[PDB]
Image (cartoon, rainbow, N blue to C red):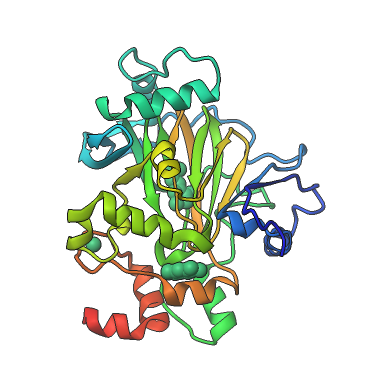
Length: 327
Ligand SMILES: Cc1cc2nc[nH]c2cc1C
Ligand SMILES: O=C(O)CNC(=O)C(=O)O
Ligand code: NI
Ligand SMILES: [Zn+2]
């Protein structure tokens, strides 16, 4: 078996290898990349997402989210308080203000220490889940707005035709902005391109060990666990690497820099934080190997977790018992 220790692998495709997206994902998996739950892909040196990021300041963040923490430094939840709309230019200015800017630090490790020590005492503002794309329409390779759709994957594999669409989201971050422990909707893959700005640090649990994270989460957030059989779907729970280590949970970490892709694999729990002002674009996707994970995906039915229009069809076809129980 390839990659038995479930290490995060880093790939450097040539421009020739960067032409066929599906083929390269399959190649990464042939090398065991999926066992980690997360992989980094550094694009060919000749490749660009777009010519410049010069004129993005007029993008609107209709509903910026203030991420307010509760708990202790290594075990906390966050809720999102909606704020008034602001442009990306205004958001960038806010991110660089004295109140919100990245503190002095020695290196990524020092900054990581500061994040876990001090995160809960601040409430950074995140621009999340903004439908759109910053890929130039003429970018032919790894254009996250031009991927084959999950609906077409399901149709090719299973012969069922379903409603629904599949488009990218933009994420504008600042220092300490946080993404909670989660797998993707329907335990899909995701791909994430860091367009510009400061780095993003990721933590990930190997898919084969996901239940270990679930069990720890039930112990650490016992009320939440009683309220919902899949409360990590709510995307509000954080657990630090120190607490994971103390509880013997297998995980890895890596920092993504501007110009790099990350892929998360089916049922790879991940969490992380932004180092400073940045912009990422992400979208879910599927492969034939995903289908069995989609069938097994745990669902929130307490009502807290958002179920998109397109998710409906996934549940209806892959999980008809769970769907009927909904209805
Ligand atoms: C181990 C395991 C547990 C799961 N629970 C939901 N999907 C799953 C997929 C795997 C692989
Ligand atoms: O970047 C973020 O804020 C969170 N992104 C993801 O969880 C992802 O791409 O799968
Ligand atoms: Ni994700
Ligand atoms: Zn729930």
